[PDB]
Amino acid sequence: TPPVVFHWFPFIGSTISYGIDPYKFFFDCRAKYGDIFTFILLGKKTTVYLGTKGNDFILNGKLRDVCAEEVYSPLTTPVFGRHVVYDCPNAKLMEQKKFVKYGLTSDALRSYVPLITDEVESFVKNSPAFQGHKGVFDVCKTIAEITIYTASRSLQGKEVRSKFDSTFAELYHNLDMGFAPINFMLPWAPLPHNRKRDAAQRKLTETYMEIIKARRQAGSKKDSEDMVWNLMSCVYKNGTPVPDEEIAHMMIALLMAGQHSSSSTASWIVLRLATRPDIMEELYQEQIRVLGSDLPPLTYDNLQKLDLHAKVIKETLRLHAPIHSIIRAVKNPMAVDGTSYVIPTSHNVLSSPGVTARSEEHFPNPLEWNPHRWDENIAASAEDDEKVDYGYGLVSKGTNSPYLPFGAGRHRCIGEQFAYLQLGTITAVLVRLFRFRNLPGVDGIPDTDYSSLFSKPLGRSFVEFEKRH
Ligand code: HEM
Ligand SMILES: O=C(N[C@@H](Cn1ccnc1)c1ccc(Cl)cc1Cl)c1ccc(-c2nnc(-c3ccc(OCC(F)(F)F)cc3F)o2)cc1
């Protein structure tokens, strides 16, 4: 059995330490107990295996030994809906992932760029957020809006985008309640917020299902969004088309996925850029040099030439990746190849790919946000390891890499290229339109709110904006 981490009280264990700051908690535990330990997380023994080998052990674990959906389903199933994601066996997840991956081809991503640019530009023109030549804005609130508009406009389609002008705003706010910290223990309890979650889940499904049906009734296709796509990409291995309900639920899940992860990340980008005016000027000059002084429209093709924009994202993900903790249930006992250790089935296991990304071993002056450290290498997709196809195409199991913001193994992100496209596009447009600065006498960046397993800026962070024109 791995070394149990010292705590003071029963069933609180190291929850508070972990919840306040996972990374500081993991590094301290590391210095005192090595690369493997067990801490009591809300009553559950939770074995943490750190370092690249830890990530490999947990993320490349066999389906026999490690279960994800068992740990997640109580929380996510009420939110996303039935028969998708984690409310099915792995094999079905793998196909659903394949379906979405289908929907995210170059032709799809191509079409999304001018739609995303238009949303950002129209937001900046129309929102109260940025009225005036010079001002302050709430970064997280503003960025969350921009991400929801950009993702729903491109990925979700016209009808959903348009409904965010009326009811979807309130629906998604209420559905998001499902991710309340309390639902890590009572996701099944009919507390008032969960009641609102469910009402919201139901009406959201309803509307999607109406949008789908109304498409069929016109017998037509008009764009590259994931709808027209799942309607056609309905076919499962056994010949069954994905039912309208599963499509609705998949879309809900994809909106939730993008919103949480991307909005957090884009917020951090803005906050970093505000602390680093040198870097923003570089980005601006890169756009001048690589696209021209006339600053022509952003396209899928010319974005990929924005080398520093990409590194700004990569480096931000290195320090601020939204998911800090990947947890699996141990289903059959497992042992650590190089040790006497064995992990019982009363344990969960936890990987933290964020730990290696801010380690001195792998990254010199790790806590320094410097995009230029990537001058050694850049890729929006990088893989030098062996490859495994789990059902949604070939992907690296890559964990010799200390940098895994999109995870690894069968459960790894299939949103990664869309995320880059969206973050890259938002950033490029913002870089054209603005300069950002911290508020008077504020140095550096805000604290991180570690909650709901989603990192984000803590508190209400304003930065100053000035329009270039
Ligand atoms: C910066 C942006 C993003 C980050 C950092 C991110 C991170 C991750 C990580 C770490 C995982 C693995 C989770 C695990 O092992 O349990 C993952 C899985 C996934 N992500 Fe993302 N993601 C991002 C954006 C997106 C977007 C935009 C979408 C969809 C549009 C998406 C859809 C998914 C899906 C479907 C999975 C698979 C879950 C599974 O197989 O169990 N992600 N993501
Ligand atoms: O939002 C989630 N998954 C996203 C991931 N994603 C987004 C972008 N790319 C990937 C997602 C994936 C796929 C798709 Cl299709 C859509 C989405 Cl949105 C998500 C998944 C599982 C869990 C969950 N399971 N147990 C907990 C849990 C959490 C905390 C805790 O104690 C902590 C403390 F102490 F702090 F309180 C106890 C827990 F049991 O959490 C919570 C959230």
Image: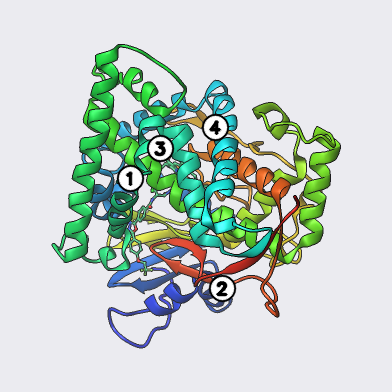
Identified by mark 4, the residue type is Leu
Q: Which residue is mark 3?
A: 161
Identified by mark 1, the residue type is Ser
Name the disc covering residue 166, or none.
Answer: 1
Mark 1 surroundings within 10 Å by alpha-carbon count, few (fewer than 14), some (14 through 19), many (20 or more): few
Q: Give yes or no for contact between labels 3 and 2 (Cβ–Cβ under 8 Å).
A: no
Mark 4 surroundings within 10 Å by alpha-carbon count, few (fewer than 14), some (14 through 19), many (20 or more): some
**Residue 408 on image: x %, y %:** 51, 44
For marks 4 and 3, the one nearer the N-term is: 4
Q: CA distance from mark 3 to mark 1?
A: 10 Å
| Secondary element at tag 2 | loop
| Secondary element at tag 3 | helix
> Which is in the foreground here, disc 3 or disc 1?
1
Instruction: Determine the residue positioned at 30% across, 72% down.
Output: 42
- Tell me, yes or no, if residue 412 can be seen here: no
Q: How is the image coloured?
A: rainbow
Q: Which residue is mark 4?
A: 115
Instruction: Determine the residue positioned at 78% across, 48% down.
Output: 283
Q: Which residue is mark 2?
A: 447
Give the image quarter of residue 461: bottom right
| Secondary element at tag 1 | loop
Identified by mark 3, the residue type is Arg
Q: Give yes or no for contact between labels 4 and 2 (Cβ–Cβ under 8 Å).
A: no
